[PDB]
């Protein structure tokens, strides 16, 4: 499902790798939405103007 | 300001997409981690491939 | 470390509640950010006025 | 408008306090949940209090 055999024989390290990925999730989203959210307000402002 | 609106819509589309993808893939990887540490949180040691 | 003796006999409910509280993390942080930046834009408008 | 600015600064302080408190507290909750789901994601069931 992720990786194709991908060292399943002893996969411990990959979990820690995923933790980094997990972290990059929040960042990658927390920024993203905010940005669009930012422009949303600006967009509204622009519309009002 | 309407041209600014057009550019803002472009940016909104780009960020919306990027966020959708990134969140999907990262959530799937997170679910993969959960499946690992749920089905095989070193439960392979109890399996032990005996 | 969390709790002092905290239903270790059957703790799954607590993991579920903490997942809910992480959903609350996301909701609250996003709401606070959007509200504060919108009212910052209102501050800017008031400044120009 | 200066009174409005003063109240707005008060509101900024309130939002920042709320955001800090919630983000810290729930981050420590995140850490605790990670410790549970890592060290004992139903490893207690493997123990089963047998």
Image (cartoon, coloured by chain):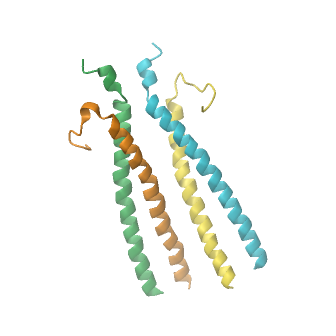
Chain colours: A orange, B green, C yellow, D cyan
**Does C12 appear above or below A43?**
above
**Does D5 appear above or below C35?**
below
**Residue at the image point whose x is 34% and y is 25% from the top:** B43
Q: List the single residue furthest toward the left.
A: A4
Q: Residue B7: which quarter of the image?
A: bottom left
D26 sits to left or right of D11: left
Residue C36 appears in the picture as rendered: yes
**Does D48 appear above or below D18?**
above
Q: How far across and how far down the image is residue A14, in percent?
A: 33, 40
Q: List the single residue furthest toward the right.
A: D3
Q: How far across and how far down the image is residue B18, in percent?
A: 36, 63
Q: List the single residue furthest toward the front.
A: A13
Q: How far across and how far down the image is residue A9, in percent?
A: 24, 31
Please state which of residues B23 and A24 is positioned toward the viewer in this rendering.
A24
B42 sits to left or right of C9: left
**Residue at the image point whose x is 64% and y is 70% from the top:** C39
Residue C17 appears in the picture as rendered: no
- Image quadrant holding the C terminus of chain A, namely bottom right
Please state which of residues B46 and C14 is positioned toward the viewer in this rendering.
B46
Q: How far across and how far down the image is residue C47, in percent?
A: 68, 81
Q: Residue D3: which quarter of the image?
A: bottom right
**Residue at the image point whose x is 45% and y is 12% from the top:** D50
**Residue at the image point whose x is 37% and y is 30% from the top:** B41
Please state which of residues D12 and C16 is positioned toward the viewer in this rendering.
D12
Please state which of residues D34 and D49 is positioned toward the viewer in this rendering.
D34
- Image quadrant holding the N terminus of chain A, namely top left
**Does C3 appear above or below A34?**
above
């Amino acid at each position: 499902r992720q990786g194709r055999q991908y060292q399943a024989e002893d996969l411990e390290a990959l979990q820690n790798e995923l933790e980094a990925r997990q972290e990059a999730l929040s960042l990658s989203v927390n920024e993203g939405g905010e940005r669009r959210m930012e422009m949303r307000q600006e967009l509204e402002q622009l519309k009002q103007k | 300001l309407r041209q600014r609106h057009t550019e803002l819509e472009r940016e909104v589309s780009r960020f919306e997409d990027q966020t959708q993808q990134q969140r999907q893939q990262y959530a799937q990887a997170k679910e993969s981690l959960t499946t690992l540490n749920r089905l095989i949180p070193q439960v392979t040691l109890l399996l032990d491939e005996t």
